[PDB]
Amino acid sequence: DIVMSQSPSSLAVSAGEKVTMSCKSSQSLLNSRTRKNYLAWYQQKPGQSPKVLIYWASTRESGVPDRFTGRGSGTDFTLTISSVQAEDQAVYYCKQAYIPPLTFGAGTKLELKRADAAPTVSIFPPSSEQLTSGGASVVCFLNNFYPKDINVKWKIDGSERQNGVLNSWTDQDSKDSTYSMSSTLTLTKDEYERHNSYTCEATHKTSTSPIVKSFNRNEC
Amino acid sequence: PGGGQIVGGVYLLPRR
Amino acid sequence: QIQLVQSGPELKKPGETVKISCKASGYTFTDFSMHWVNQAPGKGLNWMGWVNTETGEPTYADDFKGRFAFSLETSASTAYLQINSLKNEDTATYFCARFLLRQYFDVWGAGTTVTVSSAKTTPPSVYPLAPGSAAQTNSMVTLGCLVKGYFPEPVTVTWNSGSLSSGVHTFPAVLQSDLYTLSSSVTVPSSTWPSETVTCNVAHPASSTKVDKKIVPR
């Protein structure tokens, strides 16, 4: 079993820059008679299946961008992206097929870097439909921001509520290169009927002051 | 083609 | 040109067994080895083994040696993968891929997710997310759809049947005590809403759920 070691586990570059990632095998993947190294490179984007970029260690696959280049022979190999685009965000894996079992590396995640951007925040009261069911979810969207570091805090009538909160984050955008978040607070229709103010606070980097969005159960 | 499906480049020889 | 279609998401309980397919199209099935690669949630790819299509003989990797079986139906140009005695660890995607002599995969299936759990399939509740009555009007307005309380994960969401695909954000579903909840937002110009309608289309096949929720103000 040949072991494939990839490094670094993650790389962050800004559009246009050049990036290079390595992959090393526990032994030579070179066949001295055909004189080729059977190491291949695959690209896997979120929600997709992997797609080859290079084979024979340094032969670009038909139809693959010329900014993708594989190098190396023996046990040390590298994959180079000359000018990184937004749509290159993904995890790259190398694979040896010199001797079975075919083995994959752990992969290297390519994350983009862009200008900081504040998230546009939107808050939504429970729907009359949900309220009928005796439930009550308050939703807060924090979309298109950067960097990813961000913390949301809910407050009911001025007090923080940590209980019953559910968050979710999207993967870095394909063309925007930004991140989006979703925070949902659910309560019973009853506990929700006892309070007036509901607000979610987002603390980013783009401002010393938290972006706030509230709505009162009164007018609603 | 169908003559012998080979998995492992070590088992490969140059064309001919 | 060449294609590999894979069976849909599977939901089995521990102990039961499952079998999935992978149909090849556009090439002579019998001329290329067919391989299986799996991937657990938030993990890397693992080579499972391969099946000699001209011979039917399967080769398994030490890790997938035991309760896994590669099958074949040459006439139907299809390959099958069966996993017996399912354990709460086989929860993965499972891709099928075509292998070339240059030793690399050039065609893959989309992958067939299989969930091993004892949780019960349950229909979702779809709620429209319209801003508050006292919400301030900006150049753009964000609307939302909340899908809560469903189980088998496979759930899809669209807006205006795809017409609105730019300005959308669908968040990965979060699991909470056997029940997932998901949300999706769409942003369009205020000048077009509520002038032009906006509806979210969600479908949870596992429960025969299909609904369209129009987003009405207030």
Image (spheres, helix red, strand yellow):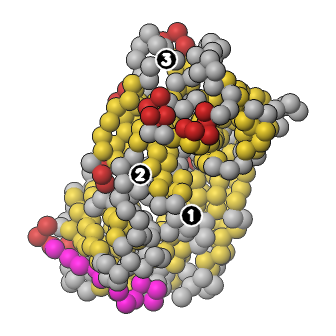
For the point 56% across and 63% down, the residue is C42
In the image, what residue occupies the spot 44% across and 23% down? C215
The residue depicted at 22 percent of the width and 58 percent of the height is: C25
> In this orientation, which residue lies closer to the viewer: A161 or C93?
A161
Numbered mark located on residue C42 in the image: 1
Q: What residue type is labelled 3?
A: Pro
Extent of the magenta region: C62-73
Which label's residue is closer to the chain start, 1 or 2?
1
Q: What residue type is labelled 2?
A: Tyr
Gap between marks 3 and 1 measured at Cα: 39 Å
Secondary element at tag 2: strand
Q: Is A186 or A1 nearer to us in this picture?
A: A186
Q: Nearer the viewer, mark 1 or mark 2?
A: 2
Q: Left of A89 or right of it: where is C101?
A: left
- Whether pointer 3 and pointer 1 mark residues with C-beta atoms closer than 8 Å, the reply is no
Q: Would you call the spot at circle 1 few (<14 residues within 10 Å), some (14-19), or many (20 or more)?
A: few
Label 3, on which residue?
C217
Would residue A42 be found to the left or right of residue C204 on screen?
right
Binning the other alpha carbons within 10 Å of mark 2 as few (below 14), some (14 to 19) or many (20 upward) gives: many
